[PDB]
Amino acid sequence: QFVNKQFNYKDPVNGVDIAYIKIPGQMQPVKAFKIHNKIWVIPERDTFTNPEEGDLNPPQVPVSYYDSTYLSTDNEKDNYLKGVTKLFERIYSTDLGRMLLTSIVRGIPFWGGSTIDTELKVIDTNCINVIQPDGSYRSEELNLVIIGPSADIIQFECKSFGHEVLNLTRNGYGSTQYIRFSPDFTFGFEESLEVDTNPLLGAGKFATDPAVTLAHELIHAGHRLYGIAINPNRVFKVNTNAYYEMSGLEVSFEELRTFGGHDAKFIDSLQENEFRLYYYNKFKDIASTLNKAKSIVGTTASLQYMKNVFKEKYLLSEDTSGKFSVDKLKFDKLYKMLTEIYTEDNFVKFFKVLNRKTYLNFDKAVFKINIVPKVNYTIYDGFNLRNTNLAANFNGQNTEINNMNFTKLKNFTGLF
Ligand SMILES: [Zn+2]
């Protein structure tokens, strides 16, 4: 199992894996759960990571959904925690998911906080502050936090804190990733491509498996933890869908990469090679920075332990004297793993689900779901339960046939 404890929300705090924490304005502490080394879950709406997003009311775009009361009660938080746990187990049960989660846990954000070259130092915004049994705070490094959505319930995304001059998600360093996510809602899509990619057609017959949606965000998180995310200012000015063109819709290269399959091929070979070279250069910077460091700051870890952590993360070569370098062959291999093997399209193949065929579509609807009961959804089958009417033809994802598992909250078709 990926998650050794089946936490209940009302389990007592212990200051270790069930604790009140603060994240790096003023905030009150929030109850959080450490589901795995380097990975925490905060069953709260995210009113914390962005100062401009401190409340839960609408400011509405077609694809949005608002309910300021979602995820306010203990029962909802208990189910949130169980649902997120189940999705991590579903992911981890696949070879591809085990690979991705292993990469994520090994992807410790770089200790790039020193302004003195000869010293190696943590960056504080890659930590959380945990209330200990005596009521005082300690600082804990972590890689990933799953948190509830902000005002728009269905705006899922990977958020992280910046640095004053460093671009941590694009300079190889990485940073702690906060994924706004809910297991309590999902998207409807259409099985015919010419309907799915038309904004005027379809009610959302099939439901997206939320394990795919979480995997998608985890793939972004992998890019961002390794500091290889593509700048969102690099976009495909889509010219393969007449409706996209009418509205001038642009899609980031980072999204196309993450989806994979034919979408990723809209990044041409020259651009692919440019980015590979750019990020290779960032890993070389990191090796040079590590070589300059002769002392560590803080008392919790030795310099040789931290140099090993980063050797293992970046797959660096180390000579006998202890000098690091980047092997271009190993770089290309890791870069390829993170960017081409870990894709939405590949997850679809492992989960054996129906899914959108492209990111360049129009979402059809949003449904309320409940994946916690095993009669509804399982680690091994998702909605498409074996030895039932739901096992065949993705019938479990068919919102018409498995109608008790989906309640439509909003239609998007006709609003674009
Ligand atoms: Zn995405």
Image (cartoon, grey):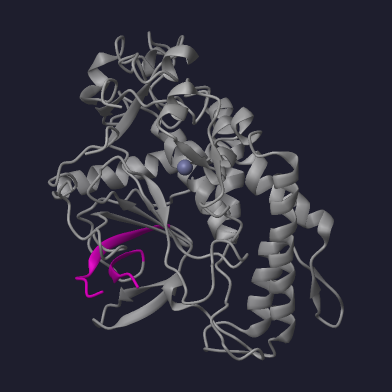
Q: Is residue 28 magenta?
A: yes
Left or right: residue 338 versus residue 411 is right
Give the residue drawn at x 35%, y 69%: 16
Left or right: residue 171 versus residue 194 is right
Residue 355 in sight from this viewpoint: no
Left or right: residue 63 versus residue 253 is left
Dividing the picture into quarters, in which one does residue 289 lie? bottom right
Placement of 17 over or under 212, stated as above or below: below
Near-viewer residue (266 or 229):
266
Q: Position of residue 220 (x, y in %)?
A: 51, 49
Q: Position of residue 107 (x, y in %)?
A: 58, 61
Dividing the picture into quarters, in which one does residue 371 lie? top left
Near-viewer residue (258 or 395):
258
Left or right: residue 3 versus residue 149 is right
Q: Position of residue 7 (x, y in %)?
A: 31, 51
- For the magenta stretch, what is the residue range? 17-35
Q: Give the number of callouts.
A: 0
Q: Is residue 359 magenta?
A: no
